[PDB]
Amino acid sequence: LAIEITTNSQEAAAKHEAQRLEQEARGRLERQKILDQSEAEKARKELLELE
Amino acid sequence: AMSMAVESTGNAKAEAESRAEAARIEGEGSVLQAKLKAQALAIETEAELE
Image (cartoon, rainbow over the protein chains, first blue to last red):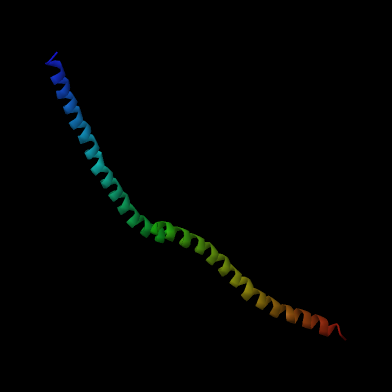
């Protein structure tokens, strides 16, 4: 029993890392999205004037 | 929001610019029409005055 809870604490801590990596990965991705959406507005407004 | 601003103004003013531009044709037209109507009534009402 003293071995299986350490492997559970192992995989739980391993899950916590991958669960953290999930957040911070999509977190920077979200900033890339807002940035790419911003560049679209810089050109869309220019297009809207021509439109 | 700058795209939202140029969207509303540029679109709505262009519609309001065309109707005013069309009204200018009626204004210049009505002047020439009333000027022609003057002759129409002048020759009508003066020649029939005899």
